[PDB]
Image 1 (tube, rainbow, N blue to C red):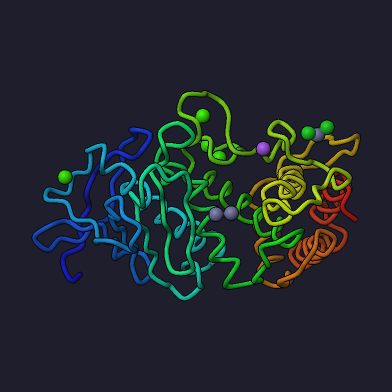
Image 2 (image 1 turned 90 degrees about the horizontal axis):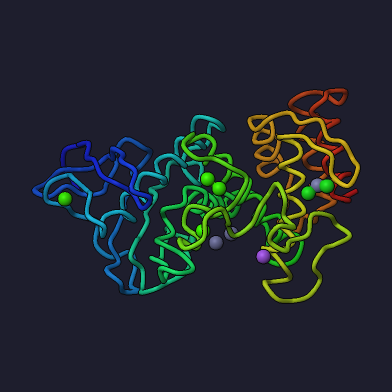
Length: 316
Ligand SMILES: [Ca+2]
Ligand SMILES: [Ca+2]
Ligand SMILES: [Ca+2]
Ligand SMILES: [Ca+2]
Ligand SMILES: [Cl-]
Ligand SMILES: [Cl-]
Ligand code: NA
Ligand SMILES: [Zn+2]
Ligand SMILES: [Zn+2]
Ligand SMILES: [Zn+2]
């Protein structure tokens, strides 16, 4: 809609307060005109038709429980935009400032969130397995990063390519969570998963095995479930990335950590310059080594640590 750019206030899914960019025209709409061609957030009102209605609020205050998932989808879409813009000079998911549209209250008891090719879609969860999924900034950014992948490398969603696809989304999901600088960690989905249970998550990048995922190529899953293990074998690459950033000794191989910003630069370059739709783990290693070489030099610590990390998780 046309209207005046305004700033509202509300509380997200975890009960934290935040200001949000809105547009005023009789009602205050979740439309943020300050980022690219706009961030728009929609109410699907428990249906499955998309996008639903552009979210309208009478008073620019979003403290109702029903408002929480809209506040977070809207705000975290903004943070994800700022991360790609400020850190990588990428304008929105497509690099051309495309509108970011999200729908919340999709369906009922729906334990999932997804990028559908055109927009973000968030279930509210069933209240046991999940609370509303837009409450997890890593989930928001993980899924928007699938759009970035589709507009770049076009990694296939099956087998080792598909596991790299998943890991890219966990890596940038986590780097956005650190960028937002409120409650970051190397777990995925900890904010929205299992409200009954403290301190768990869907998966861990620092210790994939904590949740049953492989942390070494010799443990790779080779069945056909989960599209050839895309959420499973991602642990191998997630661990390599965790090691590159933070360092550690993993199966006796020592990795010198180089920090988050350099991890992000190296993988973002690998994703946008070097990976192809069918890149496998070994080709990802080569892409990462080449990216680090381009950015830091073939004799740099950064290249040496990329190699140590991939060695540690058994990917040659
Ligand atoms: Ca209100
Ligand atoms: Ca966190
Ligand atoms: Ca997390
Ligand atoms: Ca939990
Ligand atoms: Cl470990
Ligand atoms: Cl270990
Ligand atoms: Na698991
Ligand atoms: Zn997804
Ligand atoms: Zn994913
Ligand atoms: Zn280890």
